Image (cartoon, rainbow, N blue to C red):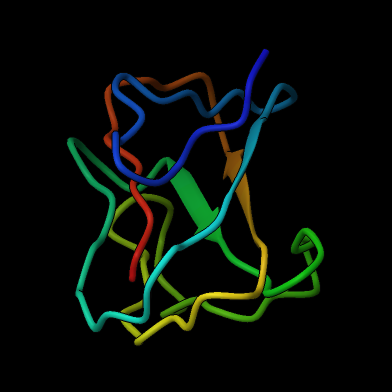
Length: 101
């Protein structure tokens, strides 16, 4: 589909043991805001990597939590593309994903 993450959070996310969801977005101005994802239980993890897309082993931002409720809070500067990666452990939807600026 398309690439969304900033402005409008992803409703009813998805965390299939096999299937996954990814998105791409960037910022306009440098602002310090704290944003995280949640809605149920730790099922879908959140990954962030400045420039390229974060892997299951490579990551730039991650509080090291269990699925949902695992986000980072840092002042992102405009000029660098941000990637999104959602990995689930088992079919489970109902989480709200958003970008942390």
